[PDB]
Amino acid sequence: MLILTRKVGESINIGDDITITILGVSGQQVRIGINAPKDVAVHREEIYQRIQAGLTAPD
Amino acid sequence: MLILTRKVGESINIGDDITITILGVSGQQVRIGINAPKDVAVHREEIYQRIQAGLTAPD
RNA sequence: GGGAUCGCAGGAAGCGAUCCC
RNA sequence: GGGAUCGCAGGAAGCGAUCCC
């Protein structure tokens, strides 16, 4: 694991094609944004489980 | 931007080599963890801006 | 043990400080 | 207008609901 600490309205980076943002919080919930090409997949765990179901390399 | 909402302790996914986790908050600041191979780089914008400065490779 | 709130930084679910129960 | 607290959900700095002043 690699950890970082920021404030609402700031960003973080991954690779050379992705960026991440903390749009804010809503109590103990957290609003998070992602900025990547359609060249990559980005989803919450609940959608991600359909991608690992047999198609992590779509048509 | 692609956006998702979570709570402290939940997680998010990217590609087939990265995962993200909201470890919790510390006021209006937030603390996040990342889970990727050394085959890719991850940093906050303040470090990332030295990498894109004209090198994209350490010493 | 948990919350609020601020700061310093890596491959570590990091590290420090303030406030409240 | 602000705070607390939660649900749904997508390529959008998205959407909804509960509680308090």
Image: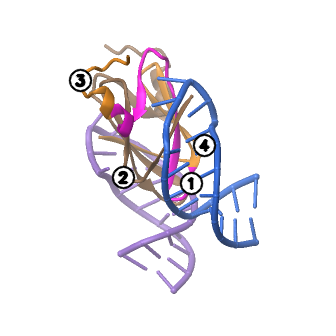
Chain colours: A brown, B orange, C blue, D purple
> Can residue B8 be seen from the camera position used here?
yes
Q: Residue at x 35, y 15 (%)?
A: A58
Please tell me whether mark 3 or mark 1 is closer to you in this view.
3
Please tell me whether mark 3 or mark 4 is closer to you in this view.
3
For the C terminus of chain A, the image quarter is: top left
Q: Which mark is residue A9?
A: 2
Chain for disc number 2: A
Determine whether the residue tagged by mark 4 lies in a helix, strand or loop.
Answer: loop
Q: How many marks?
A: 4
Determine whether the residue tagged by mark 3 lies in a helix, strand or loop.
Answer: loop
- Residue at the left extreme, as displayed: B54
Q: Residues within 10 Å of mark 1 (few under 14, many from 20)?
A: few
Q: Quadrant of residue A1?
A: top right
Q: Residues within 10 Å of mark 4 (few under 14, many from 20)?
A: few
- Say what amino acid the circle numbered 1 marks: Ser
Whether callout 2 and callout 1 share a subunit is answered no
* Mark 4, residue position: B9
Q: Which mark is residue B26?
A: 1
The stretch of residues the image draws in magenta is B25-48
Q: Position of residue D17 (x, y in %)?
A: 47, 66
Mark 4 or mark 1, earlier in chain: 4
- Say what amino acid the circle numbered 2 marks: Gly
> Can residue A12 be seen from the camera position used here?
no
Q: Residue at x 36, y 24 (%)?
A: A15
Mark 3 or mark 4, earlier in chain: 4
Determine whether the residue tagged by mark 2 lies in a helix, strand or loop.
Answer: loop
Task: Determine contact: label 3, label 1, CB under 8 Å.
Answer: no
